[PDB]
Image: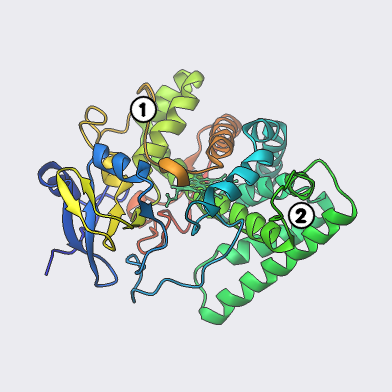
Amino acid sequence: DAPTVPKARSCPFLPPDGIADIRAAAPVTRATFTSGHEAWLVTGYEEVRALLRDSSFSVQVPHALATQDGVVTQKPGRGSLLWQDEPEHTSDRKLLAKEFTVRRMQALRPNIQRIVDEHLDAIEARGGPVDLVKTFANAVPSMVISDLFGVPVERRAEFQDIAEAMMRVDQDAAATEAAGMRLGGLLYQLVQERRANPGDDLISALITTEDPDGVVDDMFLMNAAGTLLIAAHDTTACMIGLGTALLLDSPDQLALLREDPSLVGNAVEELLRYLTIGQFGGERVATRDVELGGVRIAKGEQVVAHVLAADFDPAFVEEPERFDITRRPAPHLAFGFGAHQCIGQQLARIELQIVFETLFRRLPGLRLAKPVEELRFRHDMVFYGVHELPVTWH
Ligand code: HEM
């Protein structure tokens, strides 16, 4: 009856205490997870990469281990990617990737600058103190996605409100469901409206993409839009909030940043590694027997890629436990690895670069409004973060 995965953090910016010792002894081991099911726990950097690169592992798992019951909820179909296996994941990712290009993401920089400035304009008009989460972390990323999707500015308010409601988690089952149906309704109308009046947005591009093959219908488009939005919003928001929190709690690194603004890119990469916000890790099931770190994984067995522990493997980086923005960026696993690796990562990087540069330049002497020990952390969420971040500035 294998030991329960360490979850408790005596320091909120750092991993659960017990994890380092498991990683040093047994980087592939057995554990009991939050559902009460026992699975393979993979904590070593090399092992977690080998696991994520191995296309023997399916993403269509028998148990949701991070959850109270082992119950894998309702899954989306073609175009949603997250729960697809090859060959259909892959060809559908390929279709998506044809239009959701890194070129298209780079082309969104002016948009992101504008959105970031608009939100800061609003923050500075009010003073002082504000909740950065509500007013900035949760708002910017969904607005970036609405530009990606061609949403005109008159339509932003509704999109923002619907995206936000979808995201929040002081909510019972029905409220949660209601928020999802309100979103799906919005995206269905958005799809129709792009079919009527195409534009230069991602959805209009997907509508006319080359589709041999017959697969891009309204359903496929709704699944892709919803997954892009969902995957892009809470993750980026968590990074903005936690990354700001960790920087404000790290006046040493922040000083290095103010002394040398060219460190923003490296800061963003060190923040990604340091926070690895997918705190519980990628869930896979073997579809054949596989050998991983000398240990044999049977067909049908479930495995949890603990990307957070891997991002602190001392074989990955030296003194993994210092938060050091001067590091030359290493290949962290915050965006995953292999076939399911974050498709929007170049966009997330651009957003975070613009956010952190603009935030610290525009609000100099930004400062926590309460102590760090009073902040409330996202203990049980798929994405780790803070619920609120009260701050003031000059
Ligand atoms: C800000 C930080 C973000 C993090 C830390 C993150 C993390 C991830 C991870 C860890 C995966 C792999 C999941 C797994 O292997 O189980 C993934 C996939 C995905 N991400 Fe991100 N993401 C972030 C931002 C974004 C943005 C801006 C977008 C999209 C516009 C995005 C869109 C997606 C999509 C559709 C997938 C699934 C890809 C597939 O399954 O083939 N993410 N993300």
Q: Residue furthest right?
A: 197
Q: Is there any visible trace of residue 113 in the rendered image?
A: yes
Within 10 angstroms of label 2, few (less than 14), some, or many (20 or more) residues? some
Badge 2 is on which residue? 156
Within 10 angstroms of label 1, few (less than 14), some, or many (20 or more) residues? few
Q: Residue furthest front?
A: 212
Question: Is residue 218 rendered to the left or right of residue 256?
Answer: right
Badge 2 amino acid:
Arg
Q: Is residue 63 above or below residue 375?
A: below
Q: Considering depth in this image, is 265 or 316 the residue closer to the camera? A: 316
Point out the image quarter for the N terminus: bottom left
Instruction: Give the secondary structure at mark 1.
Output: loop
The residue at 18%/61% (across/down) is 31
Badge 1 is on which residue? 330
Q: How is the image coloured?
A: rainbow
The image quarter containing residue 364 is top right
Q: Nearer the viewer, mark 2 or mark 1?
A: 1
Point out the image quarter for the C terminus: top right
Number of labelled discs?
2
Instruction: Give the secondary structure at mark 2.
Output: helix
Counting from the top left corner in percent of width and height, residue 245 is at 42, 44
Counting from the top left corner in percent of width and height, residue 319 is at 22, 30
Q: Considering depth in this image, is 16 or 23 the residue closer to the camera? A: 23
Question: Is residue 233 rendered to the left or right of residue 5?
Answer: right
Q: Considering depth in this image, is 233 or 303 the residue closer to the camera? A: 303
Mark 2 residue's CB less than 8 Å from ligand 1 = no
Badge 1 amino acid:
Ala
